View 1 (cartoon, rainbow over the protein chains, first blue to last red):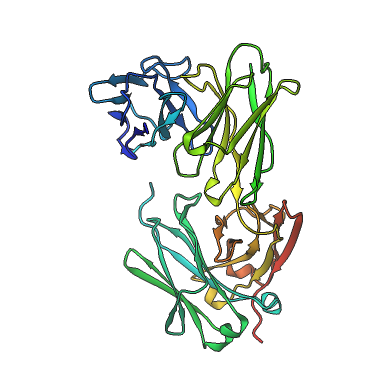
View 2: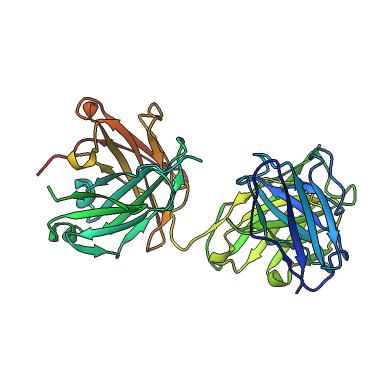
Length: 213
Length: 224
């Protein structure tokens, strides 16, 4: 029942000094060796320290680790933060024949400004209608911050059944992109006079509408 | 040096048996007196230790993963494989085969992580539908058009415009789980409205696991 406690979110501006902790609950932190792993997103983790004070060949000298055994906490000191340091940090232990990892500390460097949320609405196609299906697609692009709330409308009644939306994702031009999909039956598409998608972004609302034509 | 490469299918059905084998090149399994271990990592979560093996029959497993991890070493093929039983939807994690020099110490060499997805459906092809631009689809001097990919299994699906000739303004969105099992996404491109009726735009959606390639032309909407 030994678990390593790590700060979930840690942020610091480049060039300063930050300390990442790793606290053990039951077992003492000087009992077993502690290994810190720095893992890039979409990449294999790499060992950046070993034996709790020794730096492997290849890593910079700044990856310095210290042990505070009185508080049962393992510390990893980072000096001179850079761009490439933004990665997930995990601390390792062994306990007793059962390797236990840490919670995970993400390094934040501590970015484009607000961006207009261009909105496009697409009606269902005739080929989809012949397949006894219908889908309303709302597109959300070129916006910042990456937090947009969508709300489908059937003329005036909000629509929630069959609504599928995507989390915002960063674009190539530093902005964000998102989408919303409204699964619908062919009968329900023509039952209402018009359908609309409303996008709320930083208070401002951008609305498009489509009709069966 | 030495390297660690994983194999096995990237998909597994719920309540089934997982078969992931990690092979070794540039070294020997039995020689050197080192260990092997399997470590998984869910997307957005921390690393989780599964178990460790020696070149002999010595095995130790995580208490939360006990009585479900079966790992064996075949020195003839210079590789070791892990078998998992009763896989659920919470077992979706990136599996890493890492070499371990010291049993209480660092995993010095990490293999590249294979993606394992557990979903409950039959592998089905995608349904590509055209996304017709119109007067309500343009805001200013530019318009937008795309293609809809709906009701497919599994990830990933690649969409290319004009056989890759059109890349500027193309936005491929990540997939989202539908209300019933399957996924859905779309790929759209921003274009000036002057070339709507004079240029042909064809989307190329490919689904390799189902072996389906669909080319769908995009045309402006015709009122009927």
